[PDB]
Image (tube, coloured by chain):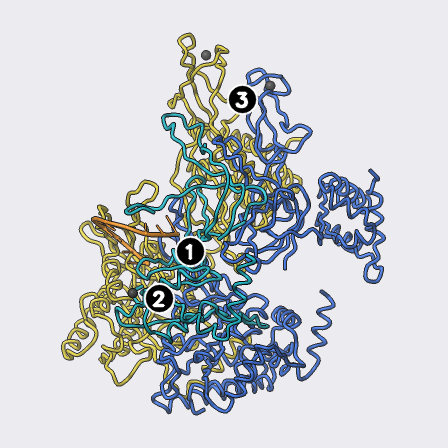
Chain colours: A blue, B yellow, C cyan, D orange
Amino acid sequence: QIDYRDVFIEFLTTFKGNNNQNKYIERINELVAYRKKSLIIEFSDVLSFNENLAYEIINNTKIILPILEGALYDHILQLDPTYQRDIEKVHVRIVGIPRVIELRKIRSTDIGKLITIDGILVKVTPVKERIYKATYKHIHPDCMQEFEWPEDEEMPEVLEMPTICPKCGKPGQFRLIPEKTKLIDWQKAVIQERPEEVPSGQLPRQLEIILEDDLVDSARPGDRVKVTGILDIKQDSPVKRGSRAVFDIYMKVSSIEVSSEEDEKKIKDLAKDPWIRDRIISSIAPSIYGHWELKEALALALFGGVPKVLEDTRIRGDIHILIIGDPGTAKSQMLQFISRVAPRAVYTTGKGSTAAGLTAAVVREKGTGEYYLEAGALVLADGGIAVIDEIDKMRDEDRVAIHEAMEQQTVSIAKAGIVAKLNARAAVIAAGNPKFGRYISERPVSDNINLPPTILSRFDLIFILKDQPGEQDRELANYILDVHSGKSTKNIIDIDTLRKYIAYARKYVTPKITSEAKNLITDFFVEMRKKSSETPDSPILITPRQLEALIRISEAYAKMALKAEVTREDAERAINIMRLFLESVGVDM
Amino acid sequence: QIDYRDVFIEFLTTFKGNNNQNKYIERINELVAYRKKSLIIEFSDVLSFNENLAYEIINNTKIILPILEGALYDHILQLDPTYQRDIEKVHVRIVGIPRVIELRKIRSTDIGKLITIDGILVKVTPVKERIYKATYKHIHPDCMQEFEWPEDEEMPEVLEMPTICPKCGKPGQFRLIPEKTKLIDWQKAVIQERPEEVPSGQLPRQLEIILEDDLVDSARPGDRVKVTGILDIKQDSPVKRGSRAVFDIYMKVSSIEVSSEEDEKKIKDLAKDPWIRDRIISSIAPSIYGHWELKEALALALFGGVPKVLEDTRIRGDIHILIIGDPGTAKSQMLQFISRVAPRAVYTTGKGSTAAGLTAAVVREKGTGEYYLEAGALVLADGGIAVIDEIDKMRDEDRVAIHEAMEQQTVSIAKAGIVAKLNARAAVIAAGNPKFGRYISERPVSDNINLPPTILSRFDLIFILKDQPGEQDRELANYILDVHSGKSTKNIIDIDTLRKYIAYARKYVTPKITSEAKNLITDFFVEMRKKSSETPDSPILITPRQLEALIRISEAYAKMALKAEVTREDAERAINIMRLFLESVGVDM
Amino acid sequence: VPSGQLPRQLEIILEDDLVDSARPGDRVKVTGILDIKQDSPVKRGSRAVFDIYMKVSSIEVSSEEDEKKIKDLAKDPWIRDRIISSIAPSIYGHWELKEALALALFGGVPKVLEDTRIRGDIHILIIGDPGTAKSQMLQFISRVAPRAVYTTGKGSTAAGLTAAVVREKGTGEYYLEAGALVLADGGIAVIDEIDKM
DNA sequence: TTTTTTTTTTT
Ligand SMILES: [Mg+2]
Ligand SMILES: [Mg+2]
Ligand SMILES: [Zn+2]
Ligand SMILES: [Zn+2]
């Protein structure tokens, strides 16, 4: 009843933020600057400013939402006249609706109301076009008339053509005119409930959501999102007789949330401590005590090196880590920790999940038989980390293709008339059990993990975990039971703060090699080759790949402290960690 | 509104090229001389001549293209009256449009405007025919009348039949008359975005394009192309009731660019250098240190020999290279460089390495349940270079399947009621590791390679790469670190001009053997046979295939310098590189 | 099921608040009205034959005196010995095996830690000579457990154990069907002749 | 995709 348009306008311009800065005006100006056409607002702010306005939004969103958008559009064009002729319709979206419904609990009483759903995206269709105002021509030798059939109404989701020509009042044949037809971007996605909320002995439920206008391509598949909108009954084919008076339901998305400058200031401040490197090492897997060398390697892997892209060649910048632990050594604890702390990670096994084990595969279409490509674990992890538990029982097909993916970081297909090349620039962290149950120290590494020696040369660092029944058993037994009761350490960095720290470093730090670091690395590599040459039965191969590992590892240390250059200290740490790796495999360095 | 066909005609004649030669006048002459029926206009020459003409072409493309084409047709008619009743309608093509949009960024606002898209062609359908003006006959005993159904309007993409006979104003049934129906050539192709612009973790997207009239068969799958035209919605099955007002997007191609006299001048200037051969060799994989003899061999395989086609036989002209080396010897890095510089190359490491994936596969056509052949790696590489990696890891039964393709350059299949032959004229470059992962000096050459002599005789050159630590490690380490520091070698022919040089040489230079070269080659072959007979323990058979390898190599050296005949120096170079290959396998001379 | 015959099936319809009142594999008692099923009325041409379906009005799955009886049993100091003696009374000996089988029926307490999860279920493997009554006890366990699934190594497949994809031919749609392991969630899965799988 | 029996190519 009461015109909230004035109330809405003053609320946007007079919203007391964290410091009465009127942040809504700031984002409105930002919207005009880049022509974003979409303004999001928080339900809490509306309720605090005027609870009566908030109730109207959450109860009569069908009626008052277009009214509010018109008021906002008038304000924007009044503020800036150049916004016209570019955007004819602005969008206002609400977030933080208190009406949260579990996906399995949806019933008929929730149809037509504004609700929010939390779940996981599984499928996303390519962007398409939907008609909301069509133009038709009456093909009747006396008419030759054009009109817009859905008069004074948006074209419904069911494509219907006129039966009587409105201009001539006659039936006949009508032809669509694409050139005078209004279109809107249209995308379809599927949301699946999280496994935590699935009841015992039941399969997870699914829901179809529709993304339109700027909401298209707002979330990659496999992301946890929060979706707000209206539910409605799907009509796949209304002309299909055969009873079936039952229908599915779908969601018209109005706002989607996935999963700051202040963070950057605190991240740079956190890097001011000269002992930041050791603090990061301590913060890695705080649950597990000891294993400092293994912890140090994992920190370097997350940061990684700087890849080099040249005119004729590309040089890998990722770091690969192999762990061979005895059963019961709890090798899966920090692996789960790595997945959580990594900004982007993929968890899988040796056999993979789909037909494409790790690299890729070519699959005939089920309906038409056409050949297409399915991405493997390595491809899906591009730009991030690929954690592969149980590396020793990969598919036989992948045992050869993994050579190229782990070194050239590409997957090449020349099968069934399809030629393609897929990027696989992903750091690989893998764990495998010894082939003889328990690791044997005297035996080499190749005959202990059941992998070709060529693969071993592709791993920057290899570590062996042995369940030694020493004095630590009592402490380990106490430690295991303490984890059962619950305990934590002190003076660490939480995963949430650490995750953004790693992400910031990987996006803005590209260390460069200095002359002093260059000389130190050169001498060690020459020393490395001499030692391996003397022993005619070296358990490991010392190839030029090892020299690349020294460069990559040293860069990660500089990146760990957000250093612009690589100095002697970074190089010295890189040499020392490689020295321990050679001792672990049994090489007298 | 003012007209511009006078300006358009004026521009065609009054435009001045780089040397004021009026190329468009010359281009018109070529169009008349060869009855080309299509003209190409560079956009950079339109706004320079008249900026006003540029925008109206871009904006009002639909209502200005027929006007300009009609004016040009009259200009051709006066230039050559006989052009009439040979080509009734002419087309003009505009290239270099400033509006370039990434495939993933196409939205609703882009429909109906002239845009440009860069991508990769993946598949092309066979040429078909489309009706744009139909003729019908009213089957009603009174009528017996014939007419063209779509009056003063081109036939729409949806085939629509009249409901009322225009000649008699009555309903009934109508019969199409194919003899009086006007047709236009029609072809459908699919374009794919380049891997560079694909976001990480996502599969590349595709778009459907339509080529009509002379644009058909202007490109082949696997080509980097730049396409220009207008987008539209796809009404594939409008008769399919059941709602679904959602439509796809396809592209109406107006002009296409694949992949210049100035290039010819640059190429000819390079050939004038007496040491052009050395420069080309030095330009092969500059980032790799050493391996000069291997770099020389790779250059020869890029150019190849001269195939001989006779009335009774065919002789292979391609050169095959085999590389065996220890892990981490830059085998894969050098092979990846070949695919960048080769005009056409195919890569296959581990997937598709079976017999079916390498030559051809018999797959059941699920559309009709029958069988048909699918091209393999070698067939897809016909006319180019096939690169095979990790050949030693292939199964022996799978490896023998390429014996026919490597020599007879054909693939023959007799399986499941299918008997067919396919052309596989491609050069094969293969890399692999020794039998025991690393080369062992104690064992002989035969068991180190671990390949049957039947396949070894088909390789023109074989090289063994040994990673022996010594005093060269310091030089190698310095070179690698210099590469990582951004330092690059100078006086190197870059990539794209090297690719143009190879493409020009292959299709324009055909060296011939002289009497001087005949005597040198004959003498060496006799000497080679005698030496092989001396030692029966050699792992390499000296067959007549080795004699033809000398001829092929000598021709490639002449082709490398754009020479029309093989002289004494080219034969000496061919003999010298043969000596190194023989020494590399323990066969002294 | 009579001798030499296959089990029959009936279709039931749950509406309003009766939805999601049971899970697959449960033994239920259902009350309602029977009616003939019409699905394709437009499909003219013969077939005046219809199937019957049940319109559910109330459903029961599988209480005070029983709780009292249970408490009285637990009061005996030797309740543990009585329970073990009640496992497969027709089998002689095998006291140690019977004791372990009793533990698996009850199980432990699952624990959720900061990062990992500790299962409360107990896994038992039995290796014995032929004729050692191995299959007899497993049949008893599958019958006495409140929720159990009995499978055989030869009569099971990977799809049948975890989940099977069923293509809805009516609409060309894919959906999952619960396997043996999923149906046994919260219960006991019995696998006979695991070595022959 | 799925279980099944069959001939077939190819995993
Ligand atoms: Mg390699
Ligand atoms: Mg038994
Ligand atoms: Zn009309
Ligand atoms: Zn008529």
Label annotation for residue C179: 1
Mark 3 secondary-structure assignment:
strand
Q: Which residue is mark 3?
A: A173
Dots 1 and 3 on the same chain: no
Query: How busy is the neighbourhood of tag 3: few (under 14 within 10 Å), some, or many (20 plus)?
Result: some
Where residue C49 sits in the image (x, y, percent)?
A: 38, 30
Chain for mark 1?
C
Q: Is residue B254 above or below residue A437?
A: above
Count up the numbered dots.
Answer: 3
Query: From the viewer's perspective, is A307 left or right of A410?
Result: right
Q: Quadrant of ligand 3?
A: top right
Mark 1 secondary-structure assignment:
loop
* Camera-nearest residue between B6 and A469: A469
Q: Which residue is mark 2?
A: C137
Camera sees residue B278: no
At label 3, which amino acid type do we have? Gln
Question: Which comes sooner in the sequence, label 1 or label 2?
Answer: 2
* Camera-nearest residue between B262 and B41: B41
* Camera-nearest residue between B331 and B297: B331
